[PDB]
Image (tube, coloured by chain):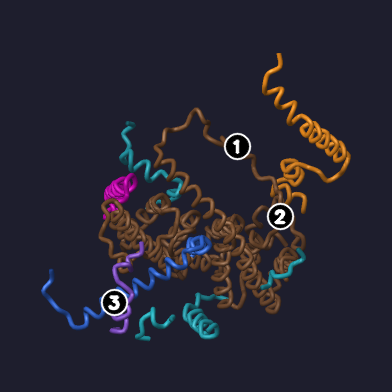
Amino acid sequence: KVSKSTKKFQSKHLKHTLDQRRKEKIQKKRIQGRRGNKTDQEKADAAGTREQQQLKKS
Amino acid sequence: TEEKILQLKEDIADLVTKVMEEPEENTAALGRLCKMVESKNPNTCKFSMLALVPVFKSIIPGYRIRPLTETEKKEKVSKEVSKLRNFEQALVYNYKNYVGRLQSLSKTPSNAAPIQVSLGILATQAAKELISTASHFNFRTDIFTLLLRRICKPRISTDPTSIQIIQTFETLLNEDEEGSISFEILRIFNKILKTRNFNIEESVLNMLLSLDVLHDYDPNTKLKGNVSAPKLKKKDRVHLSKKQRKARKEMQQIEEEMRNAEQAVSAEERERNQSEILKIVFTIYLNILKNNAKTLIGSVLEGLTKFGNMANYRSLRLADPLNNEIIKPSVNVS
Amino acid sequence: MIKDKDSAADADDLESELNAMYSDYKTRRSERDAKFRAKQARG
Amino acid sequence: LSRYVKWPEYVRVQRQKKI
Amino acid sequence: EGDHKLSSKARMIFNDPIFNNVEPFDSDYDSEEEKNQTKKEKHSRDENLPDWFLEDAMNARPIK
């Protein structure tokens, strides 16, 4: 037996939820192959510490 | 006199223990201990002056003590605050006297008896050790002046403390980002150099190479891995009354705007300090070049190469530059 | 209750009180922004 | 605090003119 | 205990690393010249009434 909340959500919010999920998937697929999309932690790891930077400068 | 030395050490230790654990109402102990430094007996002066360094390094607060005078207050309403104010004023007075004595003892023309030279060396070591943490305190200018006068001597190789003082100054300039302490040191350094017609050792001039205020790094540099609990867990909280929680919210909302304003002020002051320090450093370098000192050219050119873009013979020197293991000299090679 | 009078000491005390009032007024009026408080910290 | 509220403006002004 | 000459507190106080080896052409700096220079600089960089009455870049364009 279907619960009341399930009926309400499927009658009200299912369509836009599915559309937004599709749009998010499309955007992720589009930007998967692009170059220049990195997380802050990854950017910090690539940048290195200060001492690593004086090592690189030398 | 050896038993007298033991009795003096016992008295100093007793005073240090008396003032160490709870210094607010043991003020007279600290006052007498500081008075012992001015004693004409070399033994008392040495032992008290060397023992007072940990005392100050522990009892100096985390800020600068303002000259809070009663004229604007007219309060007379304090029970545990009045004693704190008295302790702060007495600490300022005693620290002032101690720093003055250190400065007076540092000045030794190297012609008196060796006891006075030893006194000056010990005073210089005490001042060097004190400035590592008392830089954010009153009368730092006197310590900076005496240390730089010791460093800016024409001959410093015979001094057994020049290495340590240069290392401390380099560390201070390296770890200072805002540029306040760096500018404060550079003003005195320029003032001393102008008196000596810009005549120092390449090694001395090498301290300006460590100025952090004249350095730029990656906007997203990786700091050290620092891990801490983000928030206290909800089920492990301490009970707070409604008034306590409201006061907590109010103080948090005040602290957030105070932090924002502090960041803005630091950002706007770093640029001005950087400009002033660039002016001073370039003036010093150009005056050295015009004087044409054969033993200072390489360091000057290295400084210009390092700090040029921020603007609008190793056996002939001691005290290799700070972080020399990674700072490969661009122009001042061997 | 104090039954004593001074000629110039009263005027000097009045001047000191006025100076303290003006200084407190200046500080209160200038502390309306947190930037001044932050600057005073490093002052 | 702001203790100036112990003096009204007219009193403060008439004492400032005394100086 | 160990039967030392100094007391335990005195032993702790005087065994700190600061108590190391602690056992009981030519020129001298010209303070007068620097004082005169500071006075000249102060002159080159710039009474009974109350205060409430009287008052009433080399880093501008770097490469970045």
Decide which of tag 2 and tag 1 comes sooner along the chain. 2
Disc 2 is placed on an element classified as loop
Region rendered in magenta: B1-29
Disc 3 is placed on an element classified as helix
Q: Quadrant location of residue B33?
A: bottom left
The x, y position of residue A45, in whole percent, is 74, 42
**In the visual, does B119 lie left or right of A23?**
left
The x, y position of residue B164, in whole percent, is 55, 56
Residue of label 3: D11
Q: Are marks 1 and 3 in contact (CB under 8 Å)?
A: no
Indicate whether B227 appears above or below B178: above
* 10 Å crowding of disc 3: few (<14), some (14-19), many (20+): few
The one of B101 and B189 positioned closer to us in this rendering: B189
Residue drawn at x 59%, y 64% is: B269
Query: Tell me, what hue is chain C?
Result: blue
Residue drawn at x 71%, y 27% is: A9
* Residue B185 visible in rendering: yes
Residue of label 1: B227
Indicate whether B145 appears above or below D18: above
Query: Tell me, what hue is chain B?
Result: brown
The x, y position of residue B332, in whole percent, is 74, 62
Write down the chain letter for disc 2: B
User: Separation of disc 2 and disc 3 at Cα?
Assistant: 60 Å
The x, y position of residue B43, in whole percent, is 34, 56
User: At label 1, which amino acid type do we have?
Assistant: Val
Query: Tell me, what hue is chain D?
Result: purple
Residue drawn at x 31%, y 77% is: D10
Residue of label 2: B217
